[PDB]
Amino acid sequence: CWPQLRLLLWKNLTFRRRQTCQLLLEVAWPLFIFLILISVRLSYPPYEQHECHFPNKAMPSAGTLPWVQGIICNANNPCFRYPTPGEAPGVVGNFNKSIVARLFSDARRLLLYSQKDTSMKDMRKVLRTLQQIKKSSSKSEEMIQLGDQEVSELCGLPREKLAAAERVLRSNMDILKPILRTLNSTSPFPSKELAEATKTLLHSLGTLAQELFSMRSWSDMRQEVMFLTSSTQIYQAVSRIVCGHTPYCNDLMKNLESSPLSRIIWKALKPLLVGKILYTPDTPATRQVMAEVNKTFQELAVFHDLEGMWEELSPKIWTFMENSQEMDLVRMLLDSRDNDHFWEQQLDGLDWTAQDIVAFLAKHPVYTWREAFNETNQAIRTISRFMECVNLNKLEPIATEVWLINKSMELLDERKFWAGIVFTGITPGSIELPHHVKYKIRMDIDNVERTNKIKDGYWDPGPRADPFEDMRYVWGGFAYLQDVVEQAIIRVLTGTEKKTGVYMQQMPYPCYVDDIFLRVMSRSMPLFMTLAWIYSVAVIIKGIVYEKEARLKETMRIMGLDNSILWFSWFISSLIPLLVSAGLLVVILKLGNLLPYSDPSVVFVFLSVFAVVTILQCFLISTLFSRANLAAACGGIIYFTLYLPYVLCVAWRDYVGFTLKIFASLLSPVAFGFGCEYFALFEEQGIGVQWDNLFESPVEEDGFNLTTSVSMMLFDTFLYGVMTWYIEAVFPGQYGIPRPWYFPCEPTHLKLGVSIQNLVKVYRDGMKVAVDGLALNFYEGQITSFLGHNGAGKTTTMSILTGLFPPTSGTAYILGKDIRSEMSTIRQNLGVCPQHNVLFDMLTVEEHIWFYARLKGLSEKHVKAEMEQMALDVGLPSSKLKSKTSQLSGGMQRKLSVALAFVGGSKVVILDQPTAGVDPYSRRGIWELLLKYRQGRTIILSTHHMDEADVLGDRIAIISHGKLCCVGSSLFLKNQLGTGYYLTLVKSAISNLIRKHVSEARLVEDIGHELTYVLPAFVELFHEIDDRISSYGISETTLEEIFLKVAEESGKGSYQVKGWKLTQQQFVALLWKRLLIARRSRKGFFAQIVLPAVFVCIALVFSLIVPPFGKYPSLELQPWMYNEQYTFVSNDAPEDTGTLELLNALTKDPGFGTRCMEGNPIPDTPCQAGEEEWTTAPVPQTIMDLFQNGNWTMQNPSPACQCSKMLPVCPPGAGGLPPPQRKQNTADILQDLTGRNISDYLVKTYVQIIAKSLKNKIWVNEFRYGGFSLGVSNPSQEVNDAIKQMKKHLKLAKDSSADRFLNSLGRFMTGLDTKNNVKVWFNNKGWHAISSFLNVINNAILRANLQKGENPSHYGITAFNHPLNLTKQQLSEVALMTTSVDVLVSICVIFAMSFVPASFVVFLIQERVSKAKHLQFISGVKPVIYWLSNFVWDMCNYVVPATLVIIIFICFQQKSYVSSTNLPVLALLLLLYGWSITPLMYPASFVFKIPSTAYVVLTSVNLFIGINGSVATFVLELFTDNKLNNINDILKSVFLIFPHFCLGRGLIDMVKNQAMADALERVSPLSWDLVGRNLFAMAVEGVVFFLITVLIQYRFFIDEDEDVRRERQRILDGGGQNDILEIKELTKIYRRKRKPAVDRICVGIPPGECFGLLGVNGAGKSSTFKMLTGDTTVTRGDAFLNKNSILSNIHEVHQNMGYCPQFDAITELLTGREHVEFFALLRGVPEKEVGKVGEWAIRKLGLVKYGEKYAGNYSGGNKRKLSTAMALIGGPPVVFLDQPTTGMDPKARRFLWNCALSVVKEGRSVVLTSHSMEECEALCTRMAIMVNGRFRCLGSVQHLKNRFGDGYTIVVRIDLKPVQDFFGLAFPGSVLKEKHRNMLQYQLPSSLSSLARIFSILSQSKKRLHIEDYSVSQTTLDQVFVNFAKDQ
Ligand SMILES: Nc1ncnc2c1ncn2[C@@H]1O[C@H](COP(=O)(O)OP(=O)(O)OP(=O)(O)O)[C@@H](O)[C@H]1O
Ligand SMILES: Nc1ncnc2c1ncn2[C@@H]1O[C@H](COP(=O)(O)OP(=O)(O)OP(=O)(O)O)[C@@H](O)[C@H]1O
Ligand SMILES: *[C@@H]1O[C@H](CO)[C@@H](O[C@@H]2O[C@H](CO)[C@@H](O)[C@H](O)[C@H]2NC(C)=O)[C@H](O)[C@H]1NC(C)=O
Ligand SMILES: *[C@@H]1O[C@H](CO)[C@@H](O)[C@H](O)[C@H]1NC(C)=O
Ligand SMILES: *[C@@H]1O[C@H](CO)[C@@H](O)[C@H](O)[C@H]1NC(C)=O
Ligand SMILES: [Mg+2]
Ligand SMILES: [Mg+2]
C-alpha cells in the first residue's frame, strides 16, 4: 500500500508545484486576518494602570453635608494613585479643605459665640448710662456749610482757624468751649463707672471683630463666586468651592443637561431633587418610619425657609446698619486717639485694621457694608430660586402593591421616580414591629444593578471602577435610600437619637493591567476562526468533487488503486498545507502578542487536531454530492450552519449540561469553538496552557474542559470517517456499484475472458431504453470489434463492464469474476481508455505514463523501459513528453489515452473509440501497438472506422439499440450477409454500358462522386471501363456496406430581421434559454439560490432561542451568596466610648448578620454553630526580616513591591503580619485588623492570595468582598442651647419664617457631628456586596443600640433588591446583547449574499471553456446584448433570494431591519448590492478554466473582504476612544471600493440607528452619512463594472511545392474578384514555443467548390480555424471573408460564417431542437419560421429519436450531428467544418456528405477538415495537406492522385510469406508497405496498364493460395496521406 500512497503523494506534490500561487493563497488565507489582527493590536498595547485608591463616599447617616460632598467630589473615581487620608483609621473627614465645611463650622462658631455673647447688653447699658448721666448725646450760611462739611474729630479746629483767618477773634473764645469736648474723645474721662463700662464694651467689640475676621470663609466664598461669574477653569473653581484640590428651574435643569461638569454628577442628582419615593399601606409603624425618613430628608431643607428669614429680618438688619445709635457710638469708639491703639493691641497685628473696619462699616451715603449686603441678598435669592421647584415632599402613601407598581409606572412616565420601599407588615395595626423587618427596594433597572447575576462570570482584572456602568449603587440612589431606611428602622426599634456615621470605601486594586484587546479576542476568536477554514473546506470539497466527477478518481481506481489509499493520500495532501498554516498561525499568535501566556506547542497540537477534524468533515461533505458546481456552494454553507449550535449554546449559557454540550459538539464545529473560548478565558486570566492546565478549565461547571474537547474531536473524527466510508459505499453518486444497505451486517479453445449476460441499463432521465440484451463473449487472444451506431450501447456497455455505470439487469463475468460483487478484483487487472480524454492537466505526458506504470507495480527501470516502448510504438515525436497535456491537440491526447491503457500488466483492455480525430498515419502505429499486445490482453475494439475493425478485429460484433445483431469474424459476416463485387469509380450512359456488358448490374448509392455499383464477362467489362473517370477500383463486400445493411434492417428563412428587432429577438432568445436552463436544473438552483436563504433562516432560528427577559427575581442583600469570602474587622481607637459596644455586638451570638437567629430566614443557607477561638495563622520563618527591620511607621508598614503578568510577584512577607482568624458561625472567617494599615495590608494579601491560588491553576475567583473599620471622629446640646438663646432673644416670635428657619438650622447643625463611625470597605467586583455589607453593619448597629433586651438574636433587618419588571431589562445589557446578535446576523447575511452572485459566473465558464459563447458570437449576437441578458437574468436570480430573505426578516419581526423606516431602505440596499456585485463577478471567467474553482475563489474573496471590513470598521468605531478611528473613516472611503463592505456598513448603520433610537426612547437611514452613500456608491460601481466588463469583452480596443507557390503568387499579385475566402500569409505563433503552428498560408476559395484541409495531428488546422472565426489572435497576414477583413471588422465576417468546432460546444440542459431554434433566433430567423427551419435542420441530419432529448446526454455521433446542424443554420456562404465526422457511424457521415453536397450545390463553400481519407476523396473538390503549418499539394483530388501517385494499389487479407512470394513472382516491382499480421498492401506503378489483367491473374490464383479477401483501388488517398506523413 506504500508505493501507491507515495505515488499519489508525489502527484499531489507535482500538482502543488505547478500551481504555487494557489498553495500560497491557501496557506496565507488565515495569515491575512491574523496580520490585520496583530497590526491593530500593535496600536493598542496593554495599558499599565497604576495602583490607585478610591475616596470614601459619605452616607446620609453621617450628615447631609458630607453626603452631598461625597456625591459631588468622588463622582468619577479619580484614582488619586495614593492612599487618601479618608482610608486612614484615625481621620475620616477628608473634606476639611473645602470652603463649604469651613463656612458651616464658622457659622456654628458664630452661633456659639452669640450664645456666649453679651456685647449687645454691654452697649445697651453704655447707651443707658450715657443717657442717664449726660442726657445730651444726639457769613452765616458760609460758616454753617463749612461747619457741616468739616464736622469731624479734628476738622472743627481747622474750620475755626480758617474762619478766624478772615474774621475777628469773636469766634475764637467759643472755640475754647469745643476744645474741651474734642468731638466726644475725652468725654469718658469725666465719669468713673462709664470708663469701666466703655472698656468692657471695647473688649467685647474687639473679641467680636476678631472672631468675625478670623472666620475667613465668607471672603473665599465671595472671591470664588465672583471669579466663577468660558473654559475648563470653571471646573477647578467649582471643585475648590465644593471640595478641596416653574419654567426657571426647568431652564436650569436644561442648562445642567448640557453638562458643563461631570455627567455622573447630574446623573446622581437627578433622582435626588427630582425623583420621588413611595411605600406600602399606611401602617402606623410604617408611618413613623416614613416620618423619620422625611425628617432625615428635610434636614437638608434649611434653604427652603431661608427666604422667609430673609424676607422678615432684612428690614431690621437694614435699619440696624443705617440709623441705629448703637452703631453710631460704635463708630465713635472706633476712631479716637487711643482707641486705635487699643484696637491694634487687641488685633494682635492681624489684617483688616480699624481703618478697614471703619471703611467697611461706616458709610452714610469703594467697598462697604452696602455692596456686601447686596451680594448676600443676591446669593439668598439665587439659593431660594434653586430650591424652589425641588420636590422635598417625596412621600406618597399607596394602598397595595399593584397600585404601587402602577404609580411607579406613572411617575417614571413623568421622569420623576426614586426607589420604593415595600415592607412586609402582617396587619396595619399599632404594633411596634415584628422584630424582623423584611423590606424590598424596588426601583428602575437603569439606576440599580442587575440582579439576574451576582458576579461578572469569568474572572478578569479590574476593580470595576466605572462610575456609570458598574457603580449604579452610588449614583442611582439605592445605597443612600437603603441607609436612610435602615437608620429609620433602627431609630424606631430602639429610640436612640444619636446615629453612628457610615462611610463606604471602595477596595483599591494592585496596579492591574487592562487589555480591551483581550476582551475583543475572547468575544471574536470563534468568529474570526471560521472564515479562514471555510475557505479551506470550500477548496478541499471543490477539488475532491471535481476529481471524482471528471472520472479521474474512477479511472485511477480502474488502473489499480483502491479507495483507502486515495483517501489517505487526500488526507495527507490536505493536512500538510493545513499543518504549515497552523504552524504559521501559532507563530503569529505567539509573536503578535495575541496569545502570549499560552504555550505554542499546545496551540499547535490543538490546531492540528482541529485540522484533522476539518479534513474528515470535508470528506464527509464531499461524499454527499457528485457535481462540483453544487458542492462549491454547499460545502461552506453546511460548515457554517453546523457552527450555529455553538452560538446557540453561547447565547444560552444556562440549563445546558455536560451531556447536552457533548451532543451539541457531536457535529464538532462547537468543540473547536469551546476550545477557542477556553483558550481566550485562560489568556484573559493571564495563565495560558503550559501543558498542565489541561483537564481543568471550569468557569462555572463540573467537567467540561479542554481535554474533553480534544477527546470529543477524536471521537468525532472516528465517527466522520466511519460515516464517510459508509456513505461512499452506499451513496457514491453516479459512478458506483453501489453497496447494499445491509452491509456489513465460436472458439471453444480460448480462455473466454469477458462474457456478458442480458445486460440492461436504464438512465433516470426518461428510462432511456437503450440496452435491451447482450450475450457477447470476449476471448483472450482475439480483438472483438464492438461496433454499433450512434446510441447503440457501446460506451454504456464498456462503462458497465468497468466500475462506471451499474447494470439494471443481467451480469458480466470478466475472467470468471463477476462485476456486481468482485469489482475491485477485476479492476486490479483492468485497463481502460474511454471515449473522452480523462487525464490530468498539470501533469505532462512522461509524468502521466510514469504514474500509470508505477500504479501497477513495475520497477523504476521497468517503468522507464515501458515509457520508452510506448513512446516509440504509439508515435510520439519525443518532443511532447515534457509538455503539459492541456496544450496537446485531440490526436495527441487520444494517442496518450490509448497508450495509458496498455502500460503495465492488464489482461483485460477496454478501448472506447481509440481513434477519434487521429490521422491515418498514427492510426497505423495504433494498429501495430494493438497487434503487438494481442497475446492475452483481451483487446476490445470499439471504433467507427470499418478498415480498422476489419483488419484488427478477428471476431467483430455489430449491435443496434442494445440488442445483438451479428457476431463473428469477417468471413462469417461476409459470406452470410450480402456479398458481391462493389465497383466504385469517380465521375445515364454509364449505367447502360455496364448493363449491356454484364447481366446483373444495380446502382445502390451516388453520394460525392462515388457511384457505387454492385455485381453479384467481368474481364471485358473492366476493359470497357478502362479503355473509355481514370479511376477504376473494385472490392469485395467490405465492412462499410455490411454495417450499412445491418443498420438499415434495424432553410434560412425569408425575412432576416436586423436592427432593434433582431436585438430584441436575440434578447428574448437568451432569456428563454436561461429560463430553460434554470427550469431543468432544480438541484443547482436550490443549492446556489435557495440554500443561502435557508442558511439565513436557520441562523435567525438559532438566534431566536435566546433566553427570555423581563424576569428579575428578588435578590436578598446578604453577603452569603459567595461561598468562600474573607471578612476583616478593624477596631480603631478602642476607648470604650461608642466603638467597643458595636464591636462586641458585631461578633456575638446574633452573628455577622441575620443569617441564623432563632431560625434561618434566608433560603438554602445553613450556618455553622460551633466555632469560637482566636488563633493566629502559622507564619513561616520570615519574622526576622520584619523584627530586625523594625520601627515600621504607619506609612509603608510592609516592604512595598514594584509593578513592572497581571499582578506583581515578590517574596512572602507582603502583608507583614498574619492576623488571628476566627470563624463567626457564618461560614466565613474574620481577621482582626486592630492597629494595622488597611489599604496596604489588603492590597498585599490580595496579591499573595491571587498568586498562590493561581500557581496551582484553580481558576482564581474573588478572595474578599467586604470588611468593617470602626472608629471615632475628632456638640449637640451646645448648639441646641445656642439656637434656643438666639430664638428667645432679639424679638422672639412664633411665625413660620424665623422660628422654623432657626429650628431647621439647629437640626442641620446637630446632624453633622458623629460620636462614632464605621467605614465599610467593599470590593466593587461583587455586584451586590456593598448593599449587603451595608445591611450587615446596620444590623450590627441595631443589635448594639438595643438596651437591656432578653437576647439580641431575634432582632434584625433584611433588605431585598427587586428591580422593576415594567418594560425593559437594562441599558448596557441589551446594548451589548442586541448589538452582538445583530452583528452575527449581519455577518450571516453577508455570507449568504456573497455565496449567491459568485455562481453567476459558473454558467459563464460553462460557456467560455467550450465554444458555445464563441458560437453565439459567430451569430449576429453582439457582446453587449449577451451581457445585458445575463445581467437581467442574474438580477432576477438575485432578487428571488433577496425577496426570500426579506420575507424571512419580516416573519422574524427583526425590528432592526424590517421597521417602518428600514424595510424599503434594506430592500434598496440589497438591490443595489446585487446590481453592483454582478458586473464585478462578471469579469472573472476570462482567467479561470474551471467553474467550481472560480466559484470557490470568488465566494471566498467576497466573504473575506466583506466580513473582515465590516468587523474591522465595527471594532474601530465602537471600542476605540483614540483618534485612530478617524483614519478608519478615510479607510472607509478606500473600503468603499468593495460593494460587500458597503452592504455590511449599511447593515451596521441600520443597527446602530435602531440602537440609538431605542436609547433615545429609554433619524432616517436614507441620509448621506448613512446607507444613502452606500446606495450611490453601489450604483456608480455597478455602472463602472458593467462598462469595464464590456471593455474586457472587447479587449479594451473596440522552396515549397510548385502548386503551393503558384497559388501563393496568384493570391499576392492579383486579388480574387469572386472568391469568398481569401487568406494571405496567415501566421500563428503561440507563446513560449518559438515554433509557429501555422505560417504562410495564402488560399482562395471560390463560391462553387468544396475545400478540404487535411493534415497530421498537430499540423495547424484548428489554429487556422480559430483565427478565421476569431477565437485566437492572428499574428501575420489577413483573411478576407466576403470582402471583409478580420482585424478590421469581425461582425461582418461572423454574419456570413458557419462554424463547427472540433470539440462539442453544446448546453448540457438543452435539447437538439431547442439548440437549433435558439441558434436560428440568434441569426435573425423570424419567429414565424423558427419551427420550420428547426425541423428542416433536424431532419436533414437524422436525430429523429434524439430531437427531444437533452444534448448533454447525447452520444458520440449525435453531438457531432447537432454541431453540424447548428453550423448549417442561416445558410452562410462559407461553412467551416472542423472534424465533423469524429466517432460517427457511416450513416451519419453519409448524411453529412449529403448536407455538404446540398450546401455546395446551393452556391456556397465548405472548408472541411477530417481524418478519414475516403470522405475528402469523395466529396471534397480542392484539397490541401498541411504539415507543421505548410501546405504540400494544394490541388484537386484527381490532380493529387495523378501528380503524387500512379498505377493501382492492392489490399489483400488472409500464412503470410507465400503471399509475398506470389506478389514478388507475378509482379516484378511491388513495394510492400504497411505490413500487418492480417492484411497486406502492394503498389502497381512499377508494372504495366490494363488493371483487368492483374484482376484476372489474381482471380486465377485465388484458389491455389490461402487469400481470404482482395480489393483493388486506383491510387486511393490513404496511401497518399501515409506517404505524405512518412516524408516529414
Ligand atoms: N447521462 C445520461 N443520461 C441519459 N441518457 C444517457 C446518458 N448517457 C448516455 N445516455 C444514452 O445512452 C445511449 C447509449 O449511447 P452510447 O453511449 O452507446 O453512444 P456511443 O456508442 O458512445 O455513440 P458513438 O458511437 O457515436 O460514440 C445513448 O442513446 C444516450 O442517449
Ligand atoms: N493553448 C495552447 N498552448 C500552447 N500550444 C498550443 C495551444 N493550442 C495549440 N497549441 C499547439 O498547436 C498544435 C496543434 O495545433 P492545432 O490545434 O491547429 O492542431 P489540431 O487540428 O488540434 O490537430 P488534430 O488534427 O490532431 O486535432 C500543438 O502541437 C500545440 O503545441
Ligand atoms: C416632609 O418634609 C417636607 C419637606 O421636606 C414637608 O413639606 C413642607 O410642608 C409643606 C408641605 O407639606 C410645604 O408648604 C413646605 O414648604 C414644605 N417644606 C418645609 C421646609 O416646610 C412635609 O410637610 C413633611 N411631611 C409631613 C407629613 O410633615
Ligand atoms: C481637618 O483635617 C485635617 C487633616 O488633614 C486636620 O489637620 C485639621 O486640623 C482638621 N480641621 C479641624 C479639625 O478643624
Ligand atoms: C411584573 O411583575 C408583576 C408581579 O406582581 C406582575 O403583576 C406584572 O404583570 C409584571 N409585568 C409584566 C409586564 O409582565
Ligand atoms: Mg463511443
Ligand atoms: Mg484539430
Image (cartoon, grey):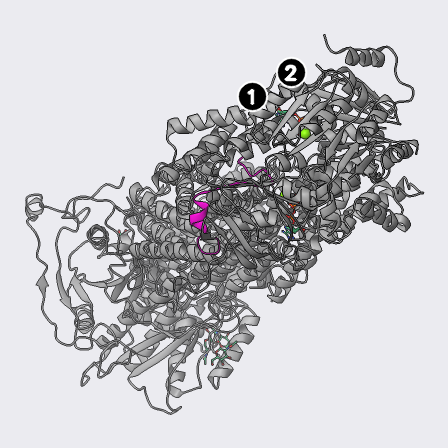
Per the image, label 2 sits on a secondary structure element best described as helix
Task: Please check the rendered image and state whether residue 825 is part of the magenta-colored stretch, yes or no.
Answer: yes
**Quadrant showing the N terminus:** top left
Provide the residue designation for mark 1.
877
Q: Which residues are magenta?
A: 819-840
Q: Position of residue 498 (x, y in %)?
A: 28, 73
> In this rendering, is residue 1679 above or below 61?
above
Residue carrying label 2: 1927
Residue 292 coordinates in the image, percent (x, y):
38, 78
Q: Quadrant of residue 1137?
A: bottom left
Image disc number at residue 1313 = none
Amino acid type shown at disc 1: Pro
When asked about the image quadrant of residue 1787, the answer is: top right
Q: Is residue 883 visible?
A: yes
SS at badge 1: loop
Q: Relative to 162, say whether 1248 is above or below.
A: below
User: Label 1 to label 2, Cα distance in Å?
Assistant: 14 Å
Q: Is residue 333 left or right of residue 1835?
A: left
Nearer the observer, 1812 or 1635: 1812
Q: Nearer the viewer, residue 1647 or 1724?
A: 1647
Locate residue 900, reporting x and y percent: 51, 34
